[PDB]
Image (tube, rainbow, N blue to C red):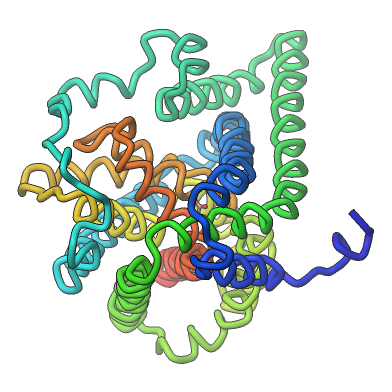
Length: 414
Ligand SMILES: N[C@@H](CC(=O)O)C(=O)O
């Protein structure tokens, strides 16, 4: 409780809890009595997970309403077309590379990391037609509460475009009312951010508890796959950086070395801060240094940062393959491309704050193939959750660099 605790700024603090916990969990004989560590520690971690889920739902709604309504109807045009194409193609290629890398490493298992035995293939997922139908909400509040992310996305975009056509109308009462509504929702969003900042400080203890249980449960071989898949992701990320950007910058006429030189400044703050939003003003400064047009970067940067996320999509595909191979599941081609589409939609919906990235994974699993209710699935989810902390660090810099690439390419064409 003592203030100095909250005064230590180092995000390295989290890693402290990562290390100190694992050691204790690693010591099976004198400390790692599975039953006692289980009963005592597990709830401290479930508390962190439970708290983490709370942040997700309203942030999506408020951020999308404000951003879409303020940004898109105003500038809507061919610039929007090129940007949308770029973002969607990048998401697709990112998930493609994640799949290819899971094929290359095969990180998931040497022997089934979950106990298997009841790995029997899951209940068949619905065909694509009903998935696409679901994207539109059968009822807004009913689907909002129950626990569905995407239809809230739809409804929010709708409401925002509506308001934006609205405020321009003549009658003053209408303009005033719309303004008040918008401001209220924006205030809600700011509040949720302020809460995120706080939760981050409790996070370390939860990391400590979760990883301690993970280590003490299975012991030595949980770290064999864990690092393997870890590297599988990191390489998969670097490739995305090298091939995608160097090609594009090369094609349109920027020498990539100087580009990354310039970006390193923002990438440092993205990696260590573990958050995408605060970098956005740093991104605007970097663009002003990069030689990019004001209206274009002012339109694109917020919209890209909220909408477009590629590194997280690769992380989700690779984590999905991890789960599948740990459970004792093997994925057919149709299921693979279905994962492609579903992960595209999930990366689109993703929130944009540190931990949220894991949560949307639960969506893809539920949308296709493996349901979450099977205990082995949650068991492996627990293993993922720990390393997610470090993986997010590189995912942040990847996403920011991709958005910068998009804006600089568009501006260079014009
Ligand atoms: N906000 C994270 C992703 C996430 O947590 O969903 C990032 O930018 O890397």
